[PDB]
Length: 267
Ligand SMILES: [Cl-]
Ligand SMILES: [Cl-]
Image (cartoon, rainbow, N blue to C red; front, top):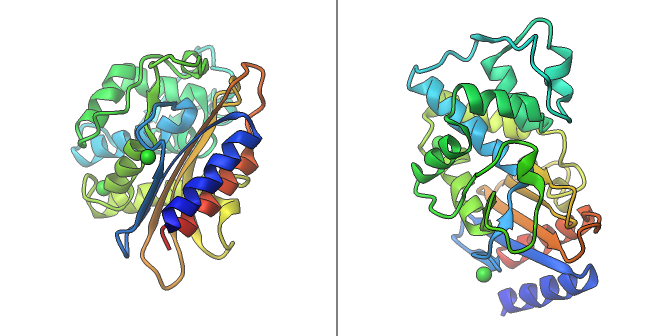
């Protein structure tokens, strides 16, 4: 009934903005979960970049790549919204810095460059998700094309549950051994695009790693986080939203508020 109560409130919340909210939350120190449309498909937007980064470290751990090798692109036409890759265009970035820019700033070139050069592309990226027990996630397009968020389109979508289970294996589990899991945890912890979403849902002295996504159509935006509360086991929160009209603005507060309700339902 604490989950029925939470469900009611998400439902109210989705009516208010005329859209669709997908939630899954896990409490790892109790097992308590909460879900709403947890297995319905949502567009990923940028949010798969949290997973690309982990793919990248997996490759370092297998010694297929070095975290410090330079990745040079001085002749490349840089994707729109490449804030980080643009200031390093003349000199290159370390593969680890490139990976992290794609995470923390949602840099589209860093993303494209990484999937074209190391990862096998969209389907390369799909393959790695398949390799951690995740059968929901799918990536079909490159960093810009994947943000169309067309209602009823299965391309570049996952379910909230799959995102959460995945982030949990990666951030908290054992796909990445010690040092490199710790790196990736640091990368999430240092994400810069998420202040008005899951971070805003929680006391500011709790520790939060997250990856946001913002399609910029269908008011489509999301966030997934690991959260370390004080004196308490980590939580996993996964929030997806779409809206009815193409020209609908995404809503940070809806995300922040659905995370507040989620976090309460698992406590
Ligand atoms: Cl559900
Ligand atoms: Cl891991």
